[PDB]
Image: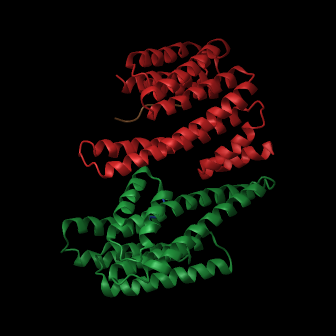
Chain colours: A red, B green, C blue, D brown
Amino acid sequence: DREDLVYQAKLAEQAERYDEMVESMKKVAGMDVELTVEERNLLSVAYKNVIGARRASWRIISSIEQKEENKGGEDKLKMIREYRQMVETELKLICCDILDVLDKHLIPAANTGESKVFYYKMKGDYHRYLAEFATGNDRKEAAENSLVAYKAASDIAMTELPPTHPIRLGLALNFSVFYYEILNSPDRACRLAKAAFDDAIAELDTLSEESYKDSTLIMQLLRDNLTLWT
Amino acid sequence: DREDLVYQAKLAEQAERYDEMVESMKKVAGMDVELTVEERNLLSVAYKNVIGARRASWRIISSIEQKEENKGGEDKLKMIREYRQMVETELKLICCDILDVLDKHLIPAANTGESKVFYYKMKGDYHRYLAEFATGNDRKEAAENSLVAYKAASDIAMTELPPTHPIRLGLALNFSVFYYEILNSPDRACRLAKAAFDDAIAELDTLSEESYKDSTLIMQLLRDNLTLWT
Amino acid sequence: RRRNSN
Amino acid sequence: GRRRNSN
């Protein structure tokens, strides 16, 4: 199976039929074993695209709702908010699907610095995506449940992974995003962004040509945010 | 009812959720009515996108299959041909779904020069998408129905639409694509495409602004195809 | 480039 | 404004 199932998940990625890519890699996750860097990323990508679609929809749907609050038309607004919530269910369903795989199947089964830090970061992201659309004491619940799960990968990263390791750098990229977006803290976002970038500069000397490539790209993203946010 | 369905189909278009957009517009098309040009376009786009995605998948899966036949790695190609055939089924079902809708509702209840041409065009396009992935007596059967539908739309277009009319150029664009891609006939493709371009140019002197935008848009698409093809 | 169809 | 980066 598992030798095949990963190829089934590769085909879905190419076909861009991510709903299958998920199902394939959930069947690999549900083996309760050490996922290879590949399997880790294939799973990672599958859910990112699936949620991605709904997230994109949501922002757009809210763009019409806000464009019809300014326009004042409060008859369409009834159907539109009916439509945004329909998505918000899927955003709830998808997020809660993957988180459920992480704390039950993946996180327990993890036994390497990378995969340990990989999954806690992941847990942060989907709690964040929950927090992205939510309101009131629903936001604060998943906001604090992310800030914990990010801070958990942060701590395990700072001993097991070097500062130039992309998984750690992507964490800081997403964590910085968490402050600027979720907690509305533009300062701590940048400080954490620049911080993550600045610690990386030193150790690039030592790493591989392909490992230098992986690091530099995520440093560009970190820098691209700091650029945009100032 | 139709008012609600059509605004739900616009929201779907914007969220790029074309599986729901198809639902909305099929419910409209069930009412056995002459569709407004908006309903016609919304219907076309919604189905165009849903088939669109499958066709892009099929192309990409067929590529991986042909790039694994040549390399000669045969054991992995067992999964791919089931995964292609799956997509082929989804295609066959979408094409069949719209054709059933065209045959049973739209064409029967279409007493208007434009709609008639539009629907016979649509019928040809979907027979063409059937012809795309088909082989043997299948490909011949679909190609015959595709052609018959384009000649049946062309006949009606040449009598009841001026050459400027975008729906007639559209038909002329997709018919040229049929010749090029399905009959493997680049000359008749170029000759048919240009012939439509070179009729509209003349009577073009005399159009409302927003029509010139339409006519010109489709003429760019004709000129590009000729450009690409030569 | 992919030939246009409408 | 072009969109922020997340990985």
- Quarter of the figure with residue A171: top right
Residue depicted at 48% across the width and 72% down the height? B177
Residue B102 visible? The answer is yes
Image position of B26 with respect to A149: above or below: below
Image position of A217 with respect to B104: above or below: above
Image position of B46 with respect to B36: above or below: above
Residue B225 visible? The answer is no
Q: Where residue A163 sits in the image (x, y, percent)?
A: 59, 16
> C3 left or right of B137?
left
> B208 left or right of A64?
left
Pick whichever, B28 or A56, lies toward us.
B28
Q: Where residue A64 sits in the image (x, y, percent)?
A: 33, 46
Residue depicted at 33% across the width and 82% down the height? B112
> A12 left or right of A59?
right
Query: Which quarter of the image is occupied by the C terminus of chain B?
Result: bottom left
Pick whichever, B112 or A189, lies toward us.
B112
Numbered disc total: 0
Query: Which quarter of the image is occupied by the N terminus of chain B?
Result: bottom left
Q: Where residue B172 sits in the image (x, y, percent)?
A: 40, 76
Residue depicted at 43% across the width and 21% down the height? A183
Pick whichever, A34 or B195, lies toward us.
A34
> B223 left or right of A149?
left
Residue depicted at 78% across the width and 32% down the height? A33
Image position of B69 with respect to B30: above or below: above
Q: Where residue B114 sits in the image (x, y, percent)?
A: 34, 79
